[PDB]
Image (tube, rainbow, N blue to C red; front, side, top):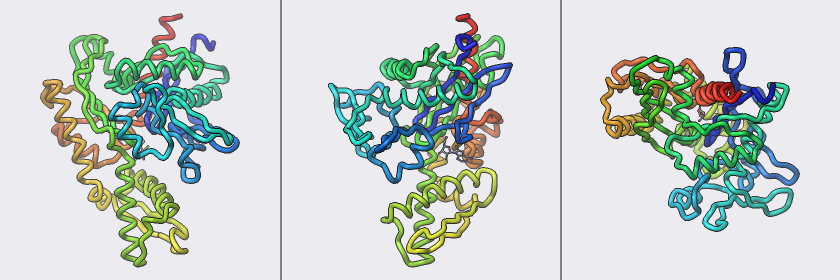
Length: 385
Ligand SMILES: Nc1ncnc2c1nc(Cl)n2[C@@H]1O[C@H](CO)[C@@H](O)[C@H]1O
């Protein structure tokens, strides 16, 4: 029943996803708001603790007590130059508890501090409760994914997050391995297979090169930009619309925090529309000083605004190929991971770099990692019996 059931969790920097393999198919489980992915946000308020969508929706009104990016802190020391650099950009407080970072917040009127693994365990508890509500019984066995470059301390702290959440962690697997499992790239019989995973998320970009030799996976190279993602494209749309508002009304909205956030969420939505339409419309009632902002943007203008950012994704691909000591023609499969890989210009640039090659993209790229983890979780729980 429950002891023979296992879930696959994609614990992401910005979004998390949960899948289950049953009756020969993977089901990506929708949350109570109908969404197949849940924001990796935890809000601490005057009355409650919010997790996910409800936490992301109140981030504007409560920025000091809304924690996100815990995956950037997990398994790291306070003194780490990565932690020190990132701290300068977060609205929540990060403190030092014996060379270990803790996030300090106000909760139910009291000052409380949390380890990154306690924050990630609250996100994991939510994913577990989403699967339980879908299945009708508690599920405790789980496969949790991590980036391929995570060291032993980061993998251990992720496993500890799973323990705190009440999960029996069957295995911690690399995100590119879960993606290659989703496409069945480990069931191609004999002979070594070279796979490139192109992972463009909300706040991070990762390129991974894997060799699959008779079922066994081997990471040959990892490259990327930890500070490049979908949110940088939204910001380029934001800057354009602020300059367009200035040309039409002779008014600068940039300093008005409410006007910029409403513009930012509308730009995120418009960006997603531009993936399947050649134009998107913004309809913001009373954006600034009672002025409605009713405009449109073509896909051509959006591609111009983000041109330099899209082209920059090809340097880590070249870097990963040189590190792996492989030429383009030696790569058997190209796999797309992350919601931003849906952008037609991103697919066009990657396909042209690989000489007109076909891309593996039939599985929702924001769900491919949870899909593969759910498959691995089923295989692992069966062998356990
Ligand atoms: N259809 C889409 N076209 C463009 N960007 C998309 C799309 N879907 C998502 Cl999600 N994203 C972005 O992916 C990230 C999450 O994986 C977010 O930045 C989201 O906007």
